[PDB]
Amino acid sequence: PALGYVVKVPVSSFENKKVDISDIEVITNGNLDDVPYKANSSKYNYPDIKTKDSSLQYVRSGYVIDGEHSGSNEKGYVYYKGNSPAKELPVNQLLTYTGSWDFTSNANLNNEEGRPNYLNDDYYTKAIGKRVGLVSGDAKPAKHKYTSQFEVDFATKKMTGKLSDKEKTIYTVNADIRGNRFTGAATASDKNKGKGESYNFFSADSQSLEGGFYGPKAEEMAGKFVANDKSLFAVFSAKHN
């Protein structure tokens, strides 16, 4: 069973202006300190690896990006991983999991797509999602905070939740629990891309939301989903209490 997944941020070109999410690799290394492709990150202008949440014992999600990206260079990777799949699951316990989520968009240089050239208030990067995919790591914490919320009913084998940006709800999640795994869908709260500085990178749904509970008594969870149109790849991890 796959311990996690890792995706490279899409990079577009002039006669390939639209490059979608692809090559979702399996992670066989379940060590939470081994960050996927960290050994390749030295060539980045600012090797930006998302902080490790030490309260998380079993799972980890985040990214490995060039935090000072330039032109058409490698942006980096988004991933999640978890070890010790749950073998005992609290039944009739109504658990609430709180954590984060991270993402990378596709790349789309087509001018008609109407992705913004400048949003310095929001991100550390220019030409948002045009040459290279937008990553959650790009956002300035003052304007964007990607948190996850999950309501899990082990009695009814049902999970609901929300992927939020600061206050705003970006996705609602629904999933069926099958053992220590879950599978389901992410529903985009906003279906319209819009245009310009109000361009919406999260307009597409996803029928491929899946992850697992990790740690003996299902103390933690992590997972991922891909947009049905490959425009986004998201990961998440959360702890219950």
Image (cartoon, rainbow, N blue to C red):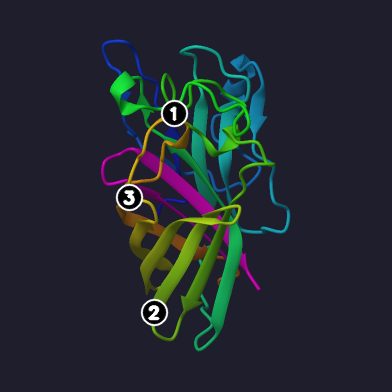
**Mark 2 crowd level (few <14, some 14–19, many ≥20, 10 Å Cα):** some
Task: Report the mark closest to the observer, 2 or 1.
Answer: 1
Looking at the image, how many numbered discs can be counted on the residues? 3
Q: What residue did someone put label 3 on?
A: 191
Quadrant position of residue 45: top right
Residue 169 is covered by the magenta coloring: no
Q: Secondary structure at mark 2?
A: loop
Q: What residue did someone put label 1 on?
A: 133
Q: Which residues are magenta?
A: 220-241
Q: Position of residue 13 (x, y in %)?
A: 34, 13
**Residue at the spot x=61%, y=52% of the render?**
166
Where does the N terminus fall, quadrant-wise? bottom left
Furthest residue to the right?
Answer: 54
Q: Identity of the amino acid at label 2?
A: Lys
Q: What residue did someone put label 2 on?
A: 157
Q: Is residue 42 something one can see in this rendering?
A: yes
Precedes in sequence: disc 2 or disc 1: 1
Q: Position of residue 137 (x, y in %)?
A: 59, 36
Please tell me whether residue 95 is drawn above or below residue 145 in the rendered image: below
**Residue at the spot x=57%, y=73% of the render?**
96
Main secondary structure type of the part rendered in magenta: strand
Q: Secondary structure at mark 3?
A: loop
Where does the C terminus fall, quadrant-wise? bottom right
Q: How far apart are the alpha carbons under marks 3 and 2?
A: 28 Å
